[PDB]
Amino acid sequence: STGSATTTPIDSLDDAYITPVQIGTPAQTLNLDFDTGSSDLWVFSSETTASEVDGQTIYTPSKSTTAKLLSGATWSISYGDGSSSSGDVYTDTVSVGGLTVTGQAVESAKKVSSSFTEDSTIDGLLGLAFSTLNTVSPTQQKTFFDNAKASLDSPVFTADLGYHAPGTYNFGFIDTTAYTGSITYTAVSTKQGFWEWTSTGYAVGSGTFKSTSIDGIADTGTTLLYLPATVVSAYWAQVSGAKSSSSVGGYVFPCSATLPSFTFGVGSARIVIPGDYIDFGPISTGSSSCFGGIQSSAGIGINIFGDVALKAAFVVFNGATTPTLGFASK
């Protein structure tokens, strides 16, 4: 089997991407944030505290003839951005772009933190990291990809995120029309539960490539590119007036600037992020200070190849017995 679904930016900055997902019988369609940095499929629901729901579409398990309470199971998750959610668990039928999994754990939120309530466009998350990170207790549950893998034509999914435009998540096949050149594959460590890999270096604009190993994660659920402070300083030093602002929480730059591109290495290959992809607009409405799309990872503990990086590439998440990642230009 295969599946193919379009993913759409939630706003004009590409702060996140939502993908329609069918849950239950008859289908209830919710727009979920596909997140290769986590491993829970959770949804706003009929059980979510009413004051914490503000415009989202909810899953109502009592209206699904295939929903079954997973007795005794609870879940609770906290994300790197400080947000969180928790609740109980049903199993139900879940379909993405024509690919159907029966018995998928659908984690129903009883509580969500303020940032989720405040984002009316995201109805939940669909985790695509390794199932060892799934938070369901006392019986850990598998991701949608893990449940579907055996049935797929090939045990892979691909992320093709658009810049200020829709893109595609495919399951079970590699669309050879969606990229240019060849796909360069690189080794993955699953030791932390992430799609964790080592970039071979970077360049800023037209500058020379610096060969240096950068361990990080391919994370569709993170908006920006988070890299070591040395790398980030080298980037922003090429933008007149750019500075790190503690009060804003990262590098900002004059909105009048033309940003240089940023290149990252995948083995001997190179992925070029155009400068425009690094502009996240005014820090506040009307400001002439703009927020940068490349930021320091120094306070995280891990480097994150988030959407800013991934959207410049066609990315293969290869879930073979030994997982690997593939990157192609497009």
Image (cartoon, helix red, strand yellow):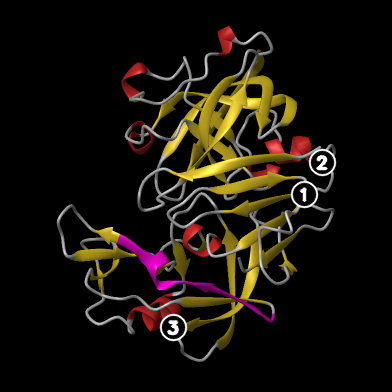
Q: Label 2's element?
A: loop
Q: Residues within 10 Å of mark 1 (few under 14, many from 20)?
A: some
Q: Which mark is residue 173?
A: 1
Q: Residue at x 63, y 54 (%)?
A: 194
Q: CA distance from mark 2 to mark 1?
A: 8 Å
Residues at discs 2 and 1 in contact (Cβ within 8 Å) = yes
Q: Which residues are magenta?
A: 268-280
Q: Label 1's element?
A: loop
The residue pinned by badge 2 equals: 152
Q: Which mark is residue 205?
A: 3
Q: Position of residue 297 (x, y in %)?
A: 44, 66
155 to 94, vertically: above or below:
below
Q: Position of residue 102 (x, y in %)?
A: 75, 23
Q: Nearer the viewer, residue 39 or 150?
A: 150
Q: Residue at x 40, y 76 (%)?
A: 232
Q: Label 3's element?
A: loop
The numbered mark, 2 or 3, whose residue comes first in the sequence reads 2
- Is 107 magenta? The answer is no
Q: Residues within 10 Å of mark 3 (few under 14, many from 20)?
A: some
Circle 3: residue type = Gly
